[PDB]
Image (cartoon, grey):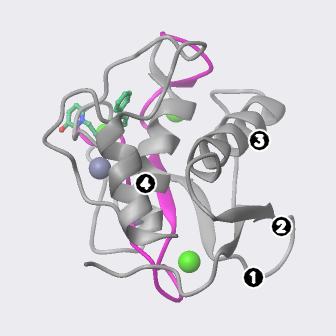
Amino acid sequence: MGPVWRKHYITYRINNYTPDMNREDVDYAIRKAFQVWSNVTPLKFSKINTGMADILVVFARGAHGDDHAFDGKGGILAHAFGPGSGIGGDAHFDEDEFWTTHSGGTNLFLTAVHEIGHSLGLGHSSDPKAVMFPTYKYVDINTFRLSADDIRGIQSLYG
Ligand SMILES: O=C(Cn1cccc(O)c1=O)NCCc1ccc(-c2ccccc2)cc1
Ligand SMILES: [Ca+2]
Ligand SMILES: [Ca+2]
Ligand SMILES: [Ca+2]
Ligand SMILES: [Zn+2]
Ligand SMILES: [Zn+2]
């Protein structure tokens, strides 16, 4: 297996907010994205407002300090680093995307579920119904669920 967090209690911080959305809508999307993974693992996620966090959430564009420049509007929407110290675990969202609460532009929640998947140590799935499938499709956020493969995946890492 790839790297995993060596503890079940994991902290996150939002470094900065996309101007695409209300601040409160960003907090909710991220919180709900961690809750999706919390619901099928022993993992507990704690939001910190100041100081050291395992998972730093970042909105940045272009070349943004890692070896993985974004590519402007479209193509790559986001990446994340698997478990580790420093940039390990951090989730980066391409600010050249139009982040939304809905089916318009790019839904932040759905993208964050995928990214936090990687932050917890998951690769991509070959199952097209998996959130860890490489490509973004909007699906109804009310009816949204992890696929059997996504649960199998994160449960093989934690519990
Ligand atoms: O950045 C991407 C997808 N993507 C799209 C167009 C062109 C690309 O080169 C490309 O990589 N993927 C990482 C983000 C991501 C992947 C899957 C999902 C997803 C959304 C809803 C249900 C299942 C998976 C969300 C976000
Ligand atoms: Ca992009
Ligand atoms: Ca980190
Ligand atoms: Ca934007
Ligand atoms: Zn990055
Ligand atoms: Zn991915």
For residue 148, what is the image quadrant?
top left
Q: Is residue 78 visible in the rendered structure shown here?
A: no
Residue 52 is tagged as 1
Up-down relation of residue 58 to residue 66 (above or below): above
Pick out the residue farthest to the front. 159
Q: Relative to 64, is 14 on the left or the right? A: right
For image coordinates 39% across by 72% down, the residue present is 82
Report if residue 9 is visible in the image.
yes
Q: Inspect the image, locate mark 2, and give the three-letter code of the amino acid beneath it.
A: Ile
Residue 33 is left or right of residue 156, and the answer is: right
Tell me: residue 55, above or below residue 14: below
Q: Earlier in the sequence, mark 3 or mark 1?
A: 3
> Neighbour class for label 4 at 10 Å: few (<14), some, many (≥20)?
many
Q: Assign the magenta stretch its main secondary structure.
A: loop
Circles 3 and 1: CB atoms closer than 8 Å: no
- The boundaries of the magenta stretch are 75-103
- The kind of secondary structure element at disc 1 is loop
Q: Are marks 1 and 2 in contact (CB under 8 Å)?
A: yes
Does residue 117 sit above or below 82 in this rendering?
A: above
Residue 82 on the magenta span? yes
Q: For mark 4, what is the residue?
A: 117
Residue 9 at x, y percent in the picture: 71, 75
Query: Amino acid type of disc 1?
Result: Met
Picture quadrant where residue 30 is located: top right
Circle 3: is it few (<14), some (14-19), or many (20+) Cα within 10 Å?
A: some
Could you tell me how far apart the alpha carbons at marks 3 and 1 are, in whole angstroms?
18 Å
Q: Which residue is mark 3?
A: 27
Point 57% across, 58% down: residue: 41
Mark 4: C-beta under 8 Å from nearest atom of ligand 6: yes
Pointer 2 residue = 48
For marks 3 and 2, the one nearer the N-term is 3
